[PDB]
Image (cartoon, rainbow over all chains, first blue to last red; front, side, top):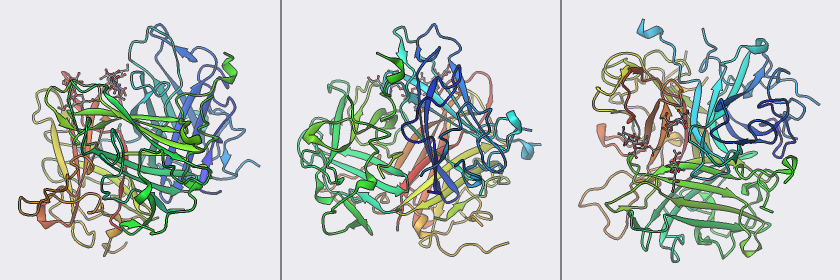
Length: 182
Length: 189
Length: 188
Ligand SMILES: CC(=O)N[C@H]1[C@H]([C@H](O)[C@H](O)CO)O[C@@](O[C@@H]2[C@@H](O)[C@H](O)O[C@H](CO)[C@@H]2O)(C(=O)O)C[C@@H]1OC(C)=O
Ligand SMILES: CC(=O)N[C@H]1[C@H]([C@H](O)[C@H](O)CO)O[C@@](O)(C(=O)O)C[C@@H]1OC(C)=O
Ligand SMILES: CC(=O)N[C@H]1[C@H]([C@H](O)[C@H](O)CO)O[C@@](O)(C(=O)O)C[C@@H]1OC(C)=O
């Protein structure tokens, strides 16, 4: 299915939050012409961020997906590449899933000011899906330079509310979209 | 694909919050291949939650869409199935649909609910949680929780549940009339 | 499955307070009977370019007004020069399939034309969310998207973006929004 690129819907541990494969990132990208429709959720399984409270610091971490100029996931990404593939051999290109570098340029007169906001999508998510357990997600397009990436999608996850009773970092699903490179 | 399953865009009262058809649920599910793109909004028209304030309790209610193995709406659902159907223009195909499995939330992504950290099942991923705004006013937050496959009622194969509520103190009564909310989810097929 | 858009890296193309004082980036993509949209706003000069608690009002309104063919009316805050389908071209002739449904989101009615037997939703034609200035989690603002709620220019359809904030900002910050995704039911 050339219209869906994903982690598979029920992944094994596939994502580094603190150490490699300590988390399960479920990410599906679906191509709707020139816009990608995405859904993302994160379950931290082991380690520092599996169960959080107010004494865990910092209260944010970053998950980078780094892509080359063919849209292939680079091995330095926090997301393990083993099962990152079209919905059904590692794929050879996925440029049409990549966030536009014209809409969302890599970092570099009022008419020369570059938007610092437009390459980010920021919202609350809710741990365990509970309305009284807000956290946040920041989706960032093409803001990384690591591994000489041509494209990137970064997920920053965190929280700010004071939690004295420890709770699993297990996020509600978040929908977003972005302008595709082609 | 690219078909829509919906309540019609201008439904008559079609949904139970407290009693049958005491509310207008507008819900459209549009298939974008492996994901469903959805928009939902609720106007409660009569009963306990039509007009809310800080003296209305509890401050949450639940609307269950329960589906069988063909993705057909079960009678126990809060939504009346009379006008829950595939789109035709601004209305519905006349005959009740026979199957809608491609519109169901995946039971692989969102399994039905059932100490080893390695076997932990995500409690978050089957829910989408956000503020909505009553009357579309920025100063009238409430909330929506969309839940996939979390019901057991009527031996459903699939479910979509909408929990609506609010937390802010409203001393003056206001209608429970939500801003539209967009979400997507992984489709069963 | 076409996209109607401002182009992804627009030149100043929008009036918040004065012509060309802002850059609105907006893409509408058709997915059958729903439009999938992404929007963001960079105010580049004037009252709302750098905001703080001493600026009032703390909301402003960007109207996209369309005629019966889905064509952008020049009265809109958005300049229509580069509002067109994604692809040297011609202004588009029709985009009704991209308009917000007037059955889902009807225009306001008069005392004359209001049916007292029907309760009309005031919320359903609005989408309301936070956006974040600079994409910083500690700089919330808000966006309100409104469908078909204008009467300006005898529009057949409209999409209105209200942007604002409520948090007290002592130190001034640029009104430069994170991107916001939404969808709506299309006219056809
Ligand atoms: C959509 C949105 O951001 N709404 C928020 C409104 C809004 O900012 C104002 O009505 C616009 O002027 O403000 C809310 O309350 C905040 C309060 O939470 C904060 O601590 O103080 C500010 C004033 O400085 C407001 O009083 C509101 O009216 O309830 C919050 C609301 O946002 C949310 C997420 O509910
Ligand atoms: C989904 C929602 O609306 N969650 C809100 C929650 C809820 O309304 C009450 O818990 C209901 O009782 O109230 C809060 O104050 C809270 O932290 O608990 C704020 C929280 O909203 C945010 C943006 O974090
Ligand atoms: C994305 C998010 O959740 N931002 C929240 C922010 C954040 O949690 C801390 O800044 C992290 O440390 O905290 C706030 O109190 C703040 O104003 O700064 C509330 C704000 O949420 C809203 C709905 O405005």
